[PDB]
Image (cartoon, rainbow over all chains, first blue to last red; front, top):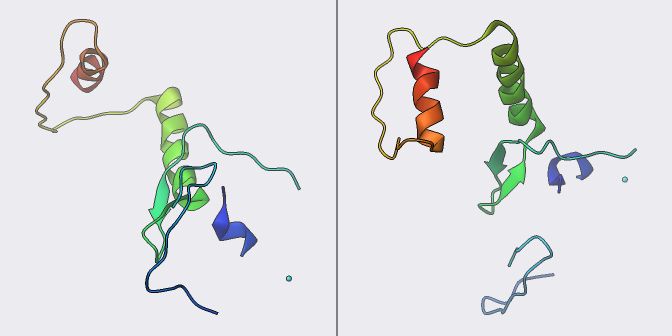
Length: 24
Length: 69
């Protein structure tokens, strides 16, 4: 909801899934 | 290394990873004018605007009267 206040690797080839907040 | 809420009406900004995340900075600067409007109003003097879809009884219809005032 607010990443701004709060705050190895990624494949090259990866799948994704959707968040409650439709995010891949 | 406090309860908070989201403003029903907020702007956003894009992350490095093109994400539209809630930006209080903007949501503020907007909502502020949005309030300033409800108070002392808001002028469009001198402005020219084109509007399509301003049918009778539509959102456009209202926005029209807006700019017309």
